[PDB]
Amino acid sequence: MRGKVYLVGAGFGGPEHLTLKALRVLEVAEVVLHDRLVHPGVLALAKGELVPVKTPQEAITARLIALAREGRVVARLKGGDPMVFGRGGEEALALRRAGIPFEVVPGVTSAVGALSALGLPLTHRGLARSFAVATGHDPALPLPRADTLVLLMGLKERLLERFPPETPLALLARVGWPGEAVRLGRVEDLPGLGEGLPSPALLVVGKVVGLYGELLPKDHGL
Amino acid sequence: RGKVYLVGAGFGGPEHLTLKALRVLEVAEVVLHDRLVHPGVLALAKGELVPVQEAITARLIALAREGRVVARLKGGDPMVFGRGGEEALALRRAGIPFEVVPGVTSAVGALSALGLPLTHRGLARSFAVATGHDPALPLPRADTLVLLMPLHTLGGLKERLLERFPPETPLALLARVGWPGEAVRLGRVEDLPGLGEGLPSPALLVVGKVVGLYGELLPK
Image 1 (cartoon, rainbow over the protein chains, first blue to last red):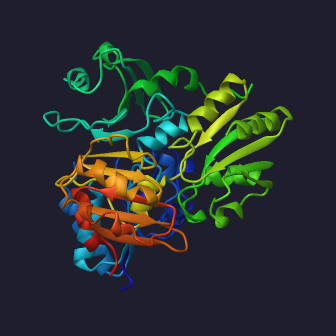
Image 2: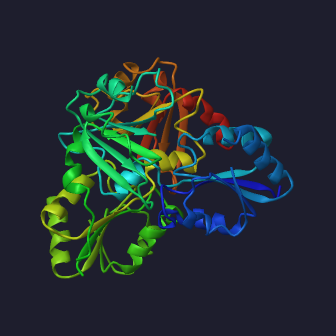
């Protein structure tokens, strides 16, 4: 087949965090079905037809398959890593089952990657040896258990079922984007500490967050 | 002008290096890199490659104070499961200018590169990452668990894993992904430790219902 689909990660922010392979794919891809919230600088590097994609997943998947069968090289461009949440695994399965050649191009994740960009650790001797990542879409279901919990996008209540009210908590919105905002406090400070924060945002809770005040500042170049 | 960059090299070849890491490798004067960083990545360093904790840090600071731009090159991401936090704290407390450059982790990146997900709306809505160096320690709890570990602790980890997952739970061992010698083993928790017999290092373990999809997702 001439057709091929690349599931591409755009990273958490600007194009400087794109991987070299991701860059190549965005140059050669004839058509790119990209998430609406993909950084402008990343989209600007795509030299094919940009197609923004709430759009039903069935439509996205069918179109990727249709395009490849037409003999085109196309890309699905997604924030962060293409396989972390965001139905990437379902897209991969569908392509495999349809007999469509495809490759997955890793990206710096929306969670872990953003925190590292700010020089913030998820683990640290004596504070945390493990971390878990989850989303806030199913408030009725239990949260995972790890020394450090990262939540993408009754909140205080549920966190209390995993951490004491005094546990350090960080809220990081639009990291790497204009309007980036970070708030440091404790679980008990919620919901107040949140309300007013831009979107989308990340939440990190656990003893390791206690180091964020000293590590958050960036090099000022002075 | 003296500054330190904590740079992630990604889990494998230069193809997974970020643009920013590429720039740091082209600009840095000295590069203190983990002795095992992919050669394809080290090849991109234009400064002097210095194969290489307490001492490491002291040297970073030392070099910076000489007014040099140095890079601490680590496999994967600079802040994930290393001493990145310790290094950053040290640099900051020493008043040294520094920037952290993220890289694709092996924990997520290596799986993604193979077209393997840690999440799926029907099979896994959370994942956790930890090391498997100390099997006496309880493991985190998530739908999908990823452990970075020495293959010699598989026997002990099996005990901790059965305390988190039914014995029939799909489990995968992925070694040297993205490197020559890449090898993948698919089985179930009950297959440990034999499932990893003869596997090369470094390797990671992934376990959970989502792992049941790996056989179909991987090429024949």
